[PDB]
Figure 1 (cartoon, rainbow, N blue to C red):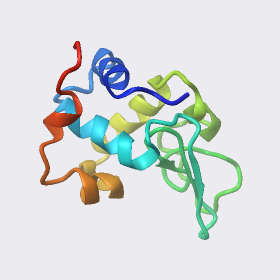
Figure 2 (figure 1 turned 120 degrees about the vertical axis):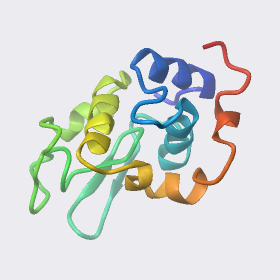
Figure 3 (figure 1 turned 90 degrees about the horizontal axis):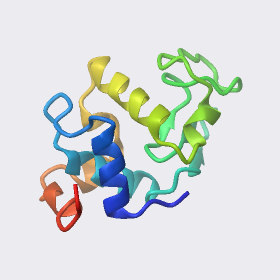
Figure 4 (figure 1 turned 45 degrees about the vertical axis):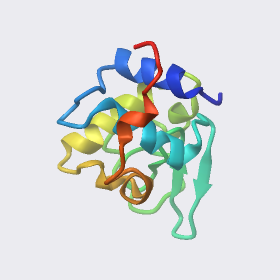
Length: 129
């Protein structure tokens, strides 16, 4: 599924991401935009044996288990295929854990590159929340 901007914002808000650990909703929408272009089935297979999965491109070395990645920690305790659903719940819950395990949103390169220092509010402006 390829989400619309406002549709994804609403879904993320229903899942409690607005101001989660001090990160406004627009940060999360902006991250998904440039990680995956809102595509829940996006995959990126890296040369190091790991794969990035889903709308938030969560990596299979630390966070989910796909059975083929060396050094898998599976800290979200889910199969990576669960992150390829049209329901974003599993990706949201694992993203929360990624932050809860010490990291900020610096854990997403696309956020560091394309969202940090910008008016992230623009990504939810105009939406019915």
